[PDB]
């Protein structure tokens, strides 16, 4: 029978001794805050500035003794979010972030629900440009581990304690997909406490293990390099007397291998360690460069042939240099793709075992 | 005869028991909100970040019993938008969005119209960077379906219910055109209700079917690839003894095919499935590569010819290798464009039937 | 003798019955608002997102009967812009716009001047990213018509009427120049009234006719294409037996024509109609491709010559094929630039007459 | 002995008749405002959108008679910047600007100092994206004159007059350097008064003469063009019978000259007048194109030689065509670099005299 | 026993004489402020606009006598950051900065802790786009010294004095790494006082010495240039009669050296001094150009050979020109890589000693 306006100005009134600046149960045990997040959107992962953009529904549960009411019989009592000025919302800030803008569209995207015993549910929707450091030791295949840290500002560990939720940890939205990565099902909850000269502060963090998909990099980078190496193999069947043809074919394959290697590393930060694509493009470039060196040795042997022919064992030395120049081409035509196939299976199995070692060590 | 200032401070006065924080007909049936949007601008569709930018006139109709007035005889009573602080505007937020900024130019772009029985018309102009996931299984021709979701924050399904309008659904502005797409005439209205641990929330969505126009991609991508394949066909008429000419022509056609294929995929996200342009550029690249292989086989047969000529059935084996080297060119000159025409009609009709299957399944 | 503070709190005081929420002469004829704009900056015209950025001094003149004062003898009475909260500024918003931010530097850039009879002068400085659709049927030469629409939000045609000024229409700043376009001297004032389900709203618009300057596109695009076609003509004087030279020259001219055509269309939206540069680059590419086809026919005739010479009317058939192979080069050397000159004068005069037809039809 | 709180609420109190909306010495002579700016940062000069970014310390000095105090004996009395709401700051706005955001970091970056007789010192730190039109008649060497205009909004010339400072004009920070330009020591102070239909408004402007440094453009653009022309000269020493070598060398030098000319104009607005780099790249391209034409004439004369040799004064006509084909190469080998050196010294001295004429006319 | 609300409204109440506009110990000695910063994130260093982005925890310690309390026995008394409106926070602003936005996510990221004797701890989290000028005299290896200046606005040296902290200077976060640079362990604390016409202002600065990592530039820039020079060395073994082969190989190596040199300088400001990569690419380009000149001299000597052979000491002059043309190739094949190795060791040791001289002079 009681009207709701006096009831919802009674608990936050200045005739009441609420004092929203003062934390609950002052001069006592620390407040325990339970947090669960809901990943609404995850994406826009950029490697060159090492950050990613999430959309989260940050839900914070804490108990306030002064907010308890015994008049109304309903337990939930969902409230309007405009009177969220004097409730004592806890301070929370993300340790590694940029941006972090609120959503003010059509209303402030906020949820306030005060239970009968004093439990408060506080939900806010925020997009954060979270910055995570990434390791690029293996660029085509890798398991990145993005770190999201939630800690407090201005309340030490003896006054405010942040804890993860027990029923579930992180709720991902159904149907959420990433175009370049695959989000793993398990998520780590390791809370570490940062120490500062001012004091220690409560901090909880969650880790997402991101598997990079290998379907795009196989089409864009691995197959055109094989096309270039196969073309340099095609140069072996051409006639050895046709010098501009073989020289031009080999030179253009080396040039396009260099430009392809320079263009695949363009969308990457300037890291100072050797990656896997470096190894792949280096061995492919070495293969086309060795093909050009093989033709240069063949044409040098033919040069020695032509100088000793035109100005005495001349016939059998002509035979020896033509037979040797034919033997080099005949053994190269078999030896080049076989050693390339050996390198391919060795590289692929060692990266398969180091990828499985990364997924086993985690 | 009554002056308007007391009348428009009477209904929102604190001597009145309006209480704009409290929802209308509290502790009763849920409020029913009818929404229709007016697409003022639609465009700026970017594939690489998978989002689009709309300009909408969001109109929300709901009934308030406390707002009803019986003194004035006029039914419409358009009001000034500055007193839109205490009216109980409903909470609405878009589920998949970025940005969503209001228009504050020369006034707040808002409309408030309170009917005599209590019906409230609330119109706001907002630009939203709506994020939609897109499928790129067929890149030149495709029918994208952009999804716009409108749901509530902080009021469950038992308290707030969102419904679409019956007289029309989505009003598009007259004369509105898209440079890259064609907006279909019908629009789906399927409302789905999202479930969360806190509770269930009302949500309505509208789907726009966007037909990608095929006029630009025919000029930019399909015809230069045909030019490259026709040039590789031109290489068959050149003399077989002119080895640097045919080798250089074929090598530059393969190189420019590779760079054209790498440059057409630049304005696209790094997806991990095979698209239609992948198939097209792959078959065209295979055609120019097979032309280079055909010349390599011709010059290998001529090599065998020259070695057996210069160091016995020599005349008729010279005839056999010259006749075979002529026969390969003569059959290739006919066989290459005919099999290319066969591939063209097969690819085009299978993509026509899969495009019509996409437009029939919807 | 009267001090100014009471006089300027008398007309906007709450002891006065001003009521700035209520429009002037309520329940009567509509308010007539006269608007003239002053183009302070115009520029930053981008084709790929189809919008332009103006800086305008929006001046709005309307009459308020309650604001009239008879105490002071001065007629102008320029006022301070801080008390522009309760004056009843009219609602105005641009129909096709993005951005539209106010200038808050060192003060709010505003002007308020209330005349003695009640005339109010309201000037504000705003930069608007106005979005205009453009037609690219002729890309090098074209006359774009940018549309600026000013309409009201929340006041129908019976309550608010917008009208253009009679003394002048749009004042452009002296010395204002555009690097890529030429602003015409006349400007259209056609007011059209938009109709919506809620009601009809007053709207006035102004059109600027922008002539695209042809000096840059002649240097960047038209002359290098002529350089490529002249180089392909140079290929006719080279010896026909030198096959790698003529083949390589023609192939590199075709390749660079393709890359030049692909690079000139890069700073343009993905439109689906044929433009004028498409026609120009297509005919130039056809010319260099026909030159390569002419050399392929010459070397095919020489191939027939060489096969019938080396394995009977042999001398006179050698004469016939050498004379025909010389005659093809001799007639091509004259016929190629003459038909190119004919195409040039036809293309140029038809685009001159369609440009003058566009400027005559307007 | 007087406490400071009553003294600093006495002069701005509503029990005082200060009335900060009303300008000082109302209904009298115009207020005289003295302005000096301090260039803290100058840079980020972009040619393609024709604007530059400054950081200025805007100091405004004006006298207020009502602010005068005779109680305290100190003359300076530096005040706190939070009570800068009611002081009657003068209206000032920059005529050609974008952005112009204030600095709100750790405090509002403001200075307020009220002298004993009524002199007010008002300093604010602002970064402005000032837009200046630039002339690109000579692109490598040029003296740009950036214009910064400071005028008033809403107060005419009879009420507000802006004047420059007498002790110094513009203070540049010590150690301030520009990477691409050199700031001259003198600065022009020409005040021009803008006239509008509403009235005339006071305006003062300052001009900075910016000398473009020529060290970068000599390395990036002038020397690689000389490398290309020297390579085309190297083509003269190669054997005339080696036709693919000389043809390929000349064709690749023409192609790379075209791409170098197209790439140096990329970071520039689309202006419609001929610049100096246009002239330089045009003459260098003409030189490499004439070298290709010279080889085409040599090989045409050799063609006439070969046709009259193989199907009578044959020996002496063979002599005449070989001697003439040798004489063309021998005279070209001397004549090409000498005429290039003549063009170089003529171009360089005429641009030196037109640069000195620009610096003498100013 | 005293409740906290009256105690925390007593010290900031208007019944108290706090007067937060007035600085502490007015008309006396200057306030001494001790500042220590905590580098939370450091990165996003861009060379082309010469600025870097930090995340700092700015801690300011100063003593206020009026804030002292003797009632409560606790010494720390951490307070809520909402009542940081009237505390007299000191004015602080960074001298060389852009941006500098506060963090408003979930709360204002602020810390307020008032000690018992009057010591105030004020911590704020800010991201600043700090602009630092950089010297690019040696581009691959260099030690940049970023300067962060903290000074006051509106309080002179006699009223406000800024001092660095004694216990530590700058705290870097543990685990913080930079992808392109290495942050040195020591940091300079040199405070310089800026002088202005208005007065002198306190300023303290901190310098970070940044070592540029050399691992990326060795892979991206130094090794492909060696590949190009090694390929030009490979051109010496090819047959001298094969003129199109050697000419084409040398010409394409010169062309790709030019494009590689133009592409490595793309991500750099337009500086006007010679860098180290300029010297490296210039010597490598000189090496490939000299190889092309060596082949041109060889083919000129062979031209003289062919003209004196075909139209008398003819046999021994044929011997002299063939022996000399062989001797040039034989001495070049040894002399080119040896002088390249000499240049490599000289360049590397002189840059090692100038890098160590830069790290010794600091
Ligand atoms: C025919 C292909 C072979 C390879 C020929 O190619 C070349 C020379 C000769 C070869 C045999 C190549 C090609 C053009 C042709 C010349 C043909 C014409 C001048 C035009 O084409 C026709 C055909 C076209 O329908 C395939 C048809 O479009 C319709 C489609 C739509 O209605 C269904 C509608 O929207 C509208 C009505 O228009 C239209 C009648 O125009 C010319 C306009 C084609 C565009 C040229 C393009 C310009 O930039 C492109 C690209 O940057 C590349 C690098 C160079 C050009 C090129 O590639 O040049 C290019 O692609 O010469
Ligand atoms: C003539 C064409 C053939 C192909 C010739 O081309 C080449 C060499 C010889 C060939 C026979 C090619 C060309 C230049 C010429 C040399 C000609 C001159 C030096 C200049 O040209 C004249 C002609 C021009 O009117 C067509 C005329 O403009 C007027 C137009 C307007 O009044 C109506 C007005 O705005 C103003 C008065 O100026 C003007 C008198 O200047 C030279 C300045 C031309 C520009 C050169 C350009 C620089 O970058 C361009 C591009 O990056 C490309 C890659 C290289 C250059 C080129 O392409 O070089 C380039 O295009 O040599
Ligand atoms: C040796 C030079 C000649 C020219 C050879 O070049 C080519 C083939 C054969 C020529 C004789 C060229 C070159 C690679 C070699 C093959 C050599 C190996 C595969 C690798 O190299 C070694 C040498 C390198 O120390 C110079 C050394 O790095 C250390 C430095 C640091 O410790 C001090 C530390 O960070 C870490 C330990 O790693 C390391 C052992 O790896 C290969 C990984 C080199 C990188 C290849 C690059 C990939 O993209 C680049 C570029 O896009 C270009 C276009 C193609 C590649 C290339 O240029 O290919 C490229 O540059 O083949
Ligand atoms: C879709 C393929 C279209 C081209 C195939 C259709 C072209 C084709 O059939 O080749 C004729 C030729 C044999 O000629 P022939 O029929 O007289 O025996 O084949 C080859 O030897 C090398 C071809 C290169 C084979 C390269 C295979 C990748």
Image: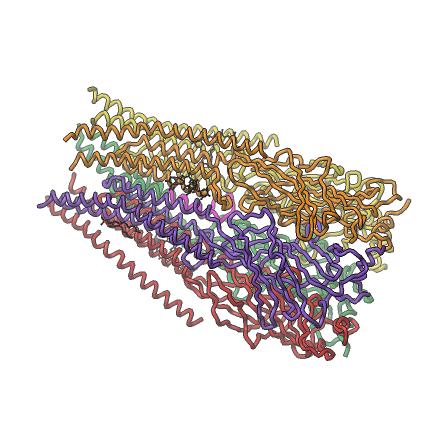
Chain colours: A red, B purple, C orange, D yellow, E green
Q: Position of residue B339 (x, y in %)?
A: 31, 49
Left or right: residue A240 versus residue D183 is left
Q: Could you say which is closer to the camera, residue E52 or residue D27?
A: D27
Answer with the quarter of the image where residue C320 lies: top left
Q: Position of residue B148 (x, y in %)?
A: 57, 59
Left or right: residue C234 versus residue E40 is left
Residue at image position (90%, 46%) is C2
Residue E260 painted magenta: yes
Task: Inspect this view and state whether residue D43 appears.
Answer: yes
Q: Could you say which is closer to the camera, residue D285 or residue C332?
A: C332
Q: Position of residue D163 (x, y in %)?
A: 74, 40
Residue B204 painted magenta: no
Left or right: residue E176 versus residue B117 is left
Which range of residues does the magenta coloring cover? Answer: E255-280
Image: D234 above or below D314: below
Answer with the quarter of the image where residue B31 lies: bottom right
Q: Furthest-top residue in view?
A: D313
Left or right: residue A26 versus residue B276 is right
Q: Could you say which is closer to the camera, residue E261 or residue C3?
A: C3
Quarter of the picture containing the N terminus of chain C is top right
Task: Inspect this view and state whether residue E283 appears.
Answer: no
């Amino acid at each position: 029978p009681m009207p709701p306006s006096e009831f919802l100005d009674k608990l936050m009134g200045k005739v009441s001794g609420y004092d929203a600046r003062i934390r609950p149960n002052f001069k006592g045990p620390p407040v325990n805050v339970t947090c669960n997040i809901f990943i609404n959107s995850f994406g826009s992962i950029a490697e060159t500035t090492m950050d990613y953009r999430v959309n989260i529904f940050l839900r914070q549960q804490w108990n306030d003794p002064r907010l308890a009411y015994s008049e109304y019989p309903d337990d939930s009592l969902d409230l309007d979010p405009s009177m969220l000025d004097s409730i004592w919302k806890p301070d929370l800030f993300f340790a590694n972030e940029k941006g972090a803008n609120f959503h003010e569209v059509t209303t402030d995207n906020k949820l306030l629900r005060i239970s009968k015993n004093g439990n408060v549910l506080y939900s806010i929707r925020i997009t954060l440009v979270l910055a995570c450091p990434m390791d690029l030791k293996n660029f085509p295949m890798d398991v990145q581990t993005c770190i999201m840290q939630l800690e407090s500002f201005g309340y030490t560990m003896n006054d405010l304690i942040f804890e993860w939720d027990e029923k579930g940890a992180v709720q991902v939205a159904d149907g959420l997909t990433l175009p370049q990565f695959i989000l793993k099902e398990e998520k780590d909850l390791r809370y570490c406490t940062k120490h500062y000269n001012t004091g220690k502060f409560t901090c909880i963090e969650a880790r997402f293990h991101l598997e990079r998909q290998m379907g795009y990099y196989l089409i864009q980078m691995y197959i055109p390099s094989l096309l270039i190496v196969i073309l340099s193999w095609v140069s072996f069947w051409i006639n050895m007397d046709a010098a501009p043809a073989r020289v031009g074919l080999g030179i253009t394959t080396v040039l396009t291998m260099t430009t392809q290697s320079s263009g695949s590393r363009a969308s990457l930060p300037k890291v100072s360690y050797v990656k896997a694509i470096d190894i792949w493009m280096a061995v492919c470039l070495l293969f086309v460069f060795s093909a050009l060196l093989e033709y240069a040795a063949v044409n040098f042997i033919a040069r020695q042939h032509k100088e000793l022919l035109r100005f005495k064992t001349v016939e059998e030395m002509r035979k020896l240099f033509i037979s040797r120049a034919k033997r080099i081409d005949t053994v190269s035509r078999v030896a080049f793709p076989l050693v390339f196939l050996i390198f391919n299976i060795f590289y692929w199995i060692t990266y398969k075992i180091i990828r499985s070692e990364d997924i086993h060590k985690q």
